[PDB]
Amino acid sequence: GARARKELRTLEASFKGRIGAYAVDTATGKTITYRSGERFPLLSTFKAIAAAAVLHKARTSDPGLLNKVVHWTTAELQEHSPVTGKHVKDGMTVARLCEAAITRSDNTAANMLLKQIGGPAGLTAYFHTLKDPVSRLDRWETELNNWSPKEKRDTTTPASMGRDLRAVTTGDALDARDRERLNAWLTANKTGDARIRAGLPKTWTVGDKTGTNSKYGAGNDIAVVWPGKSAAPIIMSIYTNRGAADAAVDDKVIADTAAILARALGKL
């Protein structure tokens, strides 16, 4: 990964920010890493793992959970609730709340998912079941998004989240039926067109989950990627921020990082 680290160092210099990147080939186990153990905010990337935790719970201890209807009041609605904002009167099933939390990053939906697994503490416990003792969710939406360089709450590392996403999308953390359902939500995501998907060939299958916060231009994207009609998947986990509180989120840097990672793993 020596060439990739130089390319990422140069890319990092070009936007005067910080890039944390992890990629793994699921067939060879080879990894590409750059600041992969540094601390970044989860932001909405946790919603992918919250859906996994819900699927795991429904499969192993709570039959019928995915069909359970959940309601919220209008006062419980969070910023960016494009789906749940339309279903205050009738509610939604837990399965549909998974779809909304992943594909539209719906914040009320994500809080509803946390209510099914013991809250932020319960998601942190699920991280532990994935052998991830690093990632920790401390707050609900939307306070969890409030990150600055010294903040330790609601953080992960590129490698920690990369290993977690690998486990649930390609490994044995989930039942094959639940793995397929999670991947179908990730590949239907509507919020990542300018990040990992933009950096990789359009014919590839990309299932991704973004995270964004305006302060310090924090921008994340994690994905499972099938690099061809018939190819072993790779996992990418990209976290970025800027050096100034008022700087912009830089989607192009995330897309360029994805291309670097795919080339370094010999897939592009």
Image (spheres, rainbow, N blue to C red):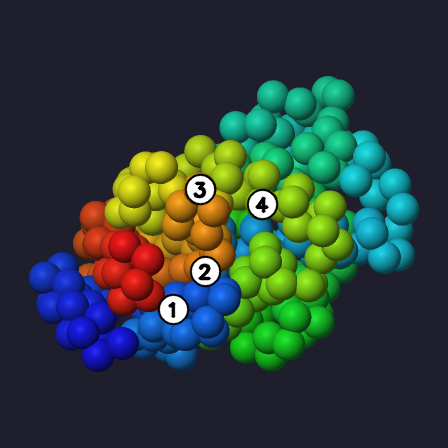
Can residue 118 be seen by looking at this rendering?
yes
Who is closer to the viewer here, 124 or 208? 208
Image quarter of residue 132 = bottom right
Residue at 59%, 35% in the rendered image: 100
Q: Could you tell me the amino acid type at mark 4?
A: Asn
When the figure is inspected, residue 210 is found, relative to residue 135, above or below; the finding is above
Who is closer to the viewer here, 217 or 251? 251
Please tell me whether mark 2 sits on a helix, a strand or a loop. strand
- Residue at the spot of label 1: 22
77 on left or right of 202? right
- Residue at the spot of label 3: 229
Question: How far apart are the two marked residues, 2 and 3, measured between alpha carbons?
Answer: 16 Å
The image shows residue 94 at horizontal and vertical percentages of: 74, 38
The first of marks 2 and 3 along the sequence is 3
Residue 98's disc is: none
Residue 183's disc is: 4
